[PDB]
């Protein structure tokens, strides 16, 4: 199963608070890993939000396939007939879903299986405060290793071969960074009250931005990728873990009663939010579509992955809770 | 015959010296005063950065005052549009607005820490003197405290013998030994009244039926506590900042100098006999002269009657108590 | 993983303990130092770091542009105010120019140059970072001074 | 998901202290800021809370104008929930439940949340222009390339939400890159006889460029009309400076208002023991833009006057145009008062 796979980028426009588990300080700690402690999004939540977006798009009928609009109302009768019109009532009764979502993003609550499995969103660039170069995208060598291991399964052509050259070792008090972050005169850079000596190297950042722009385009989520290169830093594993654990946005919130104009008793709590401008990557595994008299337009796996990439490229979607206060909006750029 | 230095970075000290020599025209008073502070060295080998030594670079005190007031007047149009917007904000709420002229000299924010050792509350953007709303609220509350202590001193002392005993014990704890001297003067009554209004508001329920005559109206203790609010209940009257009318700045100066000449300063500080061998240490400081007209506005959140009562209380306080600094010398007094 | 917060706390504790031990008898010196420490951040935010350092030097009756922190002795002043001003200037400038030490995690933003002379001919970004570091170290120093030192 | 999106512009008439409560630096009580950048922002929670409070006050006072017609919540609730119209009203009388329109727009009150979700979603008040003192042009409005890039991203999000690509490329003709000692400033700020500017601590060489500032002025004019909060927008086109990113961060971190307050005890007339504290305030005359997205209301049996999303868009725009709101703390002492203007594309 799962003949093909695709890579989905995710850029956090606004802080994201996905899910909720030690919760030592934050009453609602972010969706976090266990072995490494990096921020992450469970495949279940990403699959849910993607399938909700697909269902809403199917209702709105803006899922143009091969530069041709996809009308599901005629398609369900064409492929099912008999009770298909009655099946339409099930969509009208909200007890089911349109056939495209049922055959791609999993079945309904009640036989079959989804054509795509949504993996976890692994972190790729973490924004941290810098003394110079106001904020910097920091990574870790094992982050690059995970990226390479994940990306060996899709691209392979020459990009996969050249990506194997990424192999670095960093001490707990050393880093490699661009010209913007390194302080003038002194050969050290300060991020989040941590001082690191710059290690002389001019290949790892170049290759990282090279592959990033290679399968994400020159336009790095609405910004020129060249400007990003000057503000890329790679730190040690422990340093990256500490950054991803303690550099998130801890925001204290309260509830005020209009009767007295003060904070309600027991209404103060701290919520942890994943920082904005955070690059994350997810793997979507697509297999052979379920044999249910599928149209020849998406008969093969290549067609369905193509239509998914086309309909989800440069998209905007909300993840996690706190949607009503402008939290969770991210931009997705499918890897072509 | 004086040497001027500037502790600002290079390529900016030249412009600062041009501004202080009137070669160029500066437009922000706070900018030249604070961020471009000159250090003046007289025959004495010390770069004293004080207004007394700062004024030495001008022909006389009149030239310094004229330069400061010209710098203040150079932003009159911007201050006019700001005051128009402020008046619009006043009228947006159900705010009562009254204008008052300065009977004597006024200085607010003299105790703020600065290089000159004698600062003044100037608006950051426009560089004009103003009275913060916190000062007005505090002076109104203290005038109410003084009125209550003068009128209902013995009554509240008898009602709250426990609180007065607690205050006496605290004073004995801090103010030397003073085991039971603790004179039951008006100051102790004012202190216990403030304690009641601040930490023991609920116990003030019985006193709430009391009434005190202010000006022509009568205000209740419950009215005062509703106006100012407690740790558990928010106040109902919004006190806005006071700003001078832009029209008067065109003709009469809005800022002048004042002098303090502490003879016998070692006697006050160190303990030497006063005598007359105590050559003075003059210190100059800015102050808005008498006659300058300010606009005050108080808004309501629950009842307009409370707004009217607060306006009357604030008018009485500004007429008698006085706002700003050195109020014991008649400074910061307003007339109808 | 050596946070600069540990270096800040250690340096502040060392300097406040040093002034406490050297002038345990002079209570007024302790009070003056505590007051100057808790008022310095306001001066720095108002008039800038260079203006604050020049103000300290002027209160020390010492010329500017020809004096560095290494060539001043805080104990060589009769007046308590001068003592406290010299101690505060020495501590702040030492943290700015050397940090907690050469071998420590933080070695000072300035290599070894006098912070005032550094501010004179450096870019605005460098003096901004120096101001931020001075604010942090002054916060720690004020905390520790309020902790141990007596209050005037 | 969402259907429409409006832009709320907030011009700080008085200093604004959106409290954070996270620790305490030398400047005590810091304002809420974006952690990784340090730029001052107003989180969506506080803005939504104050908007909801103002909307509740307006509805209870019976001052909300819907379709140029006054809205009485009692009769509308009766026409919607006649079976329990009295009981629900009692909950509003006992403050258990918010009035009808606020519960439709901002969601149900805390006493019951599983019924439906809010029909509105406010956004973080990202800073757009910062007031920085200047030698000439008494104070100037300052911006950074990241600020305009985030504005372009916000415009892109609005275009995606509304499926209107025409407005997407409004700002897409502005790419800039400035050194740490360069700026693109208006003619008022530029020093006479010297191609340099002074922004409150720094001498910056005036970089020559006109398209970027003209496009920014045009974008502001389109967003907030021809009246820029009490003064014409064209009257401030010569008082705008685009500076380097680090310089803008330094301005936003160090040029903010620091206000020292004390408590005076009546026993002595002097500041009490530890009665003094410092507070951080956003400077007056600052601009913060936020996105307010709206979709289909999540309630059931809605009145015809608020049936569709556009009926919420127009109501919000008419009820929150050129209004005055209080943000953050120190309301009683005249702090945090801001002029709010609502615009659409």
Image (spheres, coloured by chain):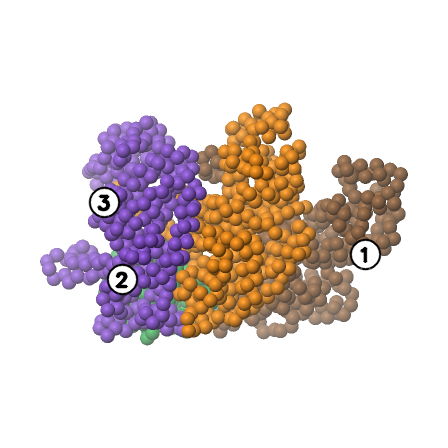
Chain colours: A brown, B purple, C green, D orange
Residue A164: give x, y in percent of width and height.
Answer: 72, 69
- In three-dimensional space, the C-alpha distance between marks 1 and 3, rounded to whole angstroms, equals 90 Å
The answer to which of marks 2 and 3 sits earlier in the sequence is 2
- In three-dimensional space, the C-alpha distance between marks 2 and 1, rounded to whole angstroms, equals 78 Å
Q: Are marks 2 and 3 on the same chain?
A: yes
Mark 2 falls within which chain? B
Q: Where residue A66 is drawn, which disc sits there?
A: 1
- In three-dimensional space, the C-alpha distance between marks 2 and 3, rounded to whole angstroms, equals 46 Å
Question: Tag 2, which secondary structure?
Answer: helix
Which residue is rendered at x = 45% and y = 37% of the image?
A261
Which residue is denoted by mark 2 in the rendering? B65
Which residue is rendered at x = 56% and y = 34% of the image?
D71
In the rendered image, the vertical position of residue B237 relative to residue D155, given as above or below: above
Q: Where residue B176 is drawn, which disc sits there?
A: 3
Judge from the rendering whether residue A216 lies leftward or rightward of residue A290; answer left or right: left
Residue C148: give x, y in percent of width and height.
Answer: 34, 54
């Amino acid at each position: 199963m799962f003949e093909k796979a695709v890579v989905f980028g995710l850029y956090s426009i606004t802080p994201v608070h996905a899910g909720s588990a030690e919760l030592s300080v934050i009453a609602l700690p972010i969706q976090r890993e266990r072995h490494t402690g990096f921020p992450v999004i469970w495949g279940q939540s990403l699959k849910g939000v993607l399938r909700s977006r697909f269902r809403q798009l199917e209702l709105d009928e803006k899922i143009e396939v091969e530069s041709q609009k996809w009308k599901w109302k005629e398609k369900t009768k064409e492929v099912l007939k008999e009770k298909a019109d009655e099946f339409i009532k099930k969509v009208e009764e909200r007890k089911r879903d349109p056939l495209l979502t049922e055959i791609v993003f999993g079945p309904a609550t009640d036989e079959h299986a989804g054509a795509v499995s949504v993996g976890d969103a692994k972190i790729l660039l973490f924004p941290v405060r810098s003394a110079k170069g106001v904020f910097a995208f920091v990574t870790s060598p094992i982050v690059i290793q995970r990226l390479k291991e994940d990306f060996e399964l899709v691209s392979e052509i020459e990009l996969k071969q050249i990506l194997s050259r990424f192999k670095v070792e960093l001490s707990n008090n050393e880093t490699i960074a661009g010209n913007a972050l390194i302080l003038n005169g002194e050969n050290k850079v300060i991020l989040e009250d941590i001082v690191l000596k710059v290690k002389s190297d001019s290949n790892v950042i170049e290759n990282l931005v090279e592959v990033l722009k290679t399968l994400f385009g020159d336009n790095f989520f609405g910004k020129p990728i060249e400007s990003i290169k000057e503000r890329i830093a790679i730190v040690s594993d422990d340093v990256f873990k500490s950054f991803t654990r303690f550099s998130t946005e801890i925001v204290a919130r309260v509830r005020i009663d209009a009767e007295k104009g003060t904070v309600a008793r027991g209404g103060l709590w701290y919520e942890e939010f994943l920082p904005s401008d955070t690059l994350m990557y997810s793997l979507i595994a697509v297999g052979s579509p379920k044999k249910e008299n599928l149209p020849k337009e998406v008969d093969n796996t290549q067609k369905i992955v193509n239509v998914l990439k086309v309909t989800f490229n440069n998209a905007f979607l909300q993840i996690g809770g706190d949607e009503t206060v402008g939290k969770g909006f991210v931009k997705v750029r499918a890897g072509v | 015959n004086v040497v001027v230095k500037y502790p600002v970075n290079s390529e900016l000290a030249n412009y600062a010296e041009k501004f202080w020599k009137k070669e160029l025209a500066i437009y922000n008073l706070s900018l030249i005063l604070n961020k471009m502070t000159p250090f003046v060295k007289r025959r004495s080998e010390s770069y004293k950065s004080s207004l007394s030594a700062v004024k030495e670079i001008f022909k006389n005190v009149d030239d310094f005052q004229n330069f400061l007031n010209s710098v203040l007047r150079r932003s009159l149009d911007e201050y006019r549009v700001f005051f128009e917007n402020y008046e619009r904000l006043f009228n947006s709420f159900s705010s009562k607005i009254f204008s008052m002229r300065t009977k004597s000299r006024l200085v607010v924010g003299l105790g703020d820490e600065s290089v000159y050792e004698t600062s003044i509350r100037l608006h950051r953007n426009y560089g004009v003197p103003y009275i913060p709303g916190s000062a007005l609220k505090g002076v109104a509350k203290h005038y109410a405290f003084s009125i209550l202590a003068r009128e209902n001193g013995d009554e509240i002392l008898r009602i709250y013998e426990s609180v007065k005993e607690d205050l006496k014990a605290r004073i004995a704890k801090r103010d030397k030994i003073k085991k039971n001297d603790v004179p039951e003067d008006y100051y102790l009554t004012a202190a216990v009244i403030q304690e009641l209004f601040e930490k023991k508001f609920d116990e003030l329920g019985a006193i709430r039926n009391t009434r005190v005559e202010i000006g022509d109206t009568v205000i209740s203790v419950g009215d005062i506590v509703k106006i100012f609010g407690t740790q558990k209940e928010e106040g109902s009257v919004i006190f806005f900042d006071a700003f001078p009318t832009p029209e008067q700045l065109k003709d009469k100066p809005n800022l002048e100098l004042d002098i303090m000449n502490p003879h016998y300063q070692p006697y006050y500080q160190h303990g030497e006999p006063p005598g007359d061998w105590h050559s003075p240490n003059p210190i100059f400081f800015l102050t808005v002269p008498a006659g300058v007209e300010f606009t005050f506005a108080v808004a309501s959140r629950d009842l307009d009657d409370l707004a009217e009562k607060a306006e009357k209380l604030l008018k009485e306080a500004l007429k008698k108590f006085g706002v700003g600094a050195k109020t014991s010398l008649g400074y910061g007094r307003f007339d109808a | 993983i050596r946070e600069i917060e540990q270096e800040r706390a250690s340096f502040a504790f060392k300097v406040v303990s040093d002034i406490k031990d050297k002038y345990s008898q002079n209570k007024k010196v302790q009070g003056k130092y505590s007051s100057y420490a808790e008022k310095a951040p306001t001066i720095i935010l108002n008039n800038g770091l260079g203006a604050t350092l020049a103000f300290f030097l002027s209160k020390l009756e010492k010329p500017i542009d020809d004096v560095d922190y290494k060539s001043i002795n805080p104990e060589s002043f009769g007046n308590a105010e001068n003592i406290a001003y010299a101690f505060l200037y020495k501590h702040l400038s030492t943290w700015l120019a050397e940090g907690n030490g050469k071998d420590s995690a933080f070695s000072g933003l300035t290599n070894g140059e006098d912070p005032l002379k550094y501010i004179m001919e450096k870019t605005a970004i460098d003096v901004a970072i120096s101001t931020e570091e001075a604010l942090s170290i002054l916060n720690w120093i004020k905390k520790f001074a309020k902790a141990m030192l007596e209050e005037e």
